[PDB]
Image 1: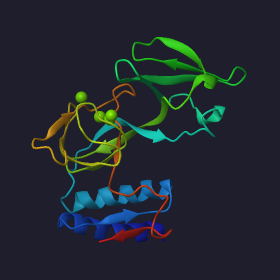
Image 2 (image 1 turned 120 degrees about the horizontal axis):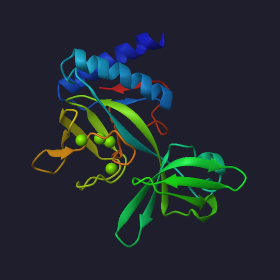
Image 3 (image 1 turned 90 degrees about the horizontal axis):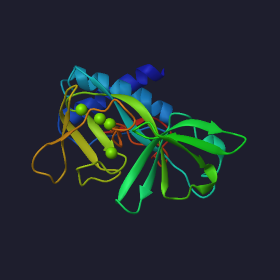
Length: 216
Ligand SMILES: [Mg+2]
Ligand SMILES: [Mg+2]
Ligand SMILES: [Mg+2]
Ligand SMILES: [Mg+2]
């Protein structure tokens, strides 16, 4: 049974993290990634590795677009976030999708000030990026995966951060090759949300096998 098998995987995975040993958890799909992640966090709390209190925050996960998909209307859903790279300002301008209009193949975008504009799905090109805002729980000791540049940090997509402490007001993280812990915001809006996701389980797609597996 799955809940039984995942409980035992979590027990092995947590015991190895507690000992400071290298350990990796893989699964074959995003649903299993969420379920095994819940089982692993429960067990890391029971084994003393992750704090019991948790803080929820909005965070962003990339939705991949390329020349074949970028102009397909249903790739866009109300409440996703889009960013456009600004060549002057060297800055990503951020919006929320309020509306996707069929007939006219148009998005209505709203900015942090609450200003809107209509963009033709047509003018998008590779200067735009799409994200899903997700709410996620974070506790003291969390392992996070970086999914994009984080304001104020030198980290990149694919880096790992370890959460040293988290509260309603700030999350402090240990940054590989940075001396001091860095303080980051605890977001409750798509406009302040950081490009992070939980990092205990690997992203699926290029795994050793289809079965949920702990390498410990
Ligand atoms: Mg904050
Ligand atoms: Mg945050
Ligand atoms: Mg965030
Ligand atoms: Mg960020």
